[PDB]
Amino acid sequence: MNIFEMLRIDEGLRLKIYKDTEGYYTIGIGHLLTKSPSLNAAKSELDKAIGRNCNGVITKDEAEKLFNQDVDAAVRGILRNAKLKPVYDSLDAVRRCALINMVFQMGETGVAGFTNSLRMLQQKRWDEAAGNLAKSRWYNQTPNRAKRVITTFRTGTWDAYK
Ligand SMILES: [Cl-]
Ligand SMILES: [Cl-]
């Protein structure tokens, strides 16, 4: 199991514009297009992103290309962030994937806001961090996905995805 297989399980694959769990315009493998309410604002963002007139539809290949960018952007953003980098460096390979997963979903700023949970991960207090992380809107909004990520951090194994 690797980061890609993990996110693909969590986000799914859709070749046509759709609305995410929060009502936003998305495509492919969890690629947010716009928080605006317009479908047209989404269709324009999409074409800017692909470099063609897509009219709201893309190929698998295009979806993958976007996914490669997003994962890379997520890893670079963690490494660049003063709050996140130290956490990432203190972690083992499995737990590292769990932090990337959060960052891809919620953005660097959002994750950087879980101060307390971040401090406990850095301290290796697995049970207590799992417990604090569950106390969030994130967990209340997408419970099955958050539980998967949380188990990843508690255990250090790929059990939830298996
Ligand atoms: Cl809460
Ligand atoms: Cl969920």
Image (cartoon, helix red, strand yellow):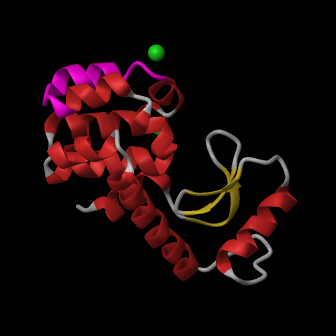
Residue found 49% across the figure and 58% down from its top: 12
Q: Quadrant of the N terminus?
A: bottom left
In the depicted structure, whether residue 18 falls above or below residue 139 = below
Q: Does 35 lie within the magenta span?
A: no
- State the residue lying farthest toward the front: 82
Place of residue 31 in the rendered image (x, y in percent of width and height, measured from the top left): 58, 60
Residue found 24% across the figure and 50% down from its top: 96
Place of residue 93 in the rendered image (x, y in percent of width and height, measured from the top left): 16, 54
Residue found 33% across the figure and 62% down from its top: 5
Place of residue 152 in the rendered image (x, y in percent of width and height, measured from the top left): 23, 41
In the depicted structure, whether residue 141 falls above or below residue 104 = above
Q: Quadrant of residue 71?
A: bottom left
Whether residue 131 sits left or right of residue 137 in the image: it is: left
Whether residue 126 sits left or right of residue 22 in the image: it is: left
Of helix, strand and loop, which mostly describes the magenta segment?
A: helix
Q: How many marks?
A: 0
Whether residue 26 sits left or right of residue 76 in the image: it is: right
Q: Quadrant of residue 59?
A: bottom right
Place of residue 80 in the rendered image (x, y in percent of width and height, measured from the top left): 37, 54
Is residue 47 in view from this perspective?
yes
What range of the chain is rendered magenta?
122-136
As rendered, which of 102 and 84 lies closer to the eye?
84
Residue found 49% across the figure and 54% down from its top: 11
Is residue 158 in view from this perspective?
no
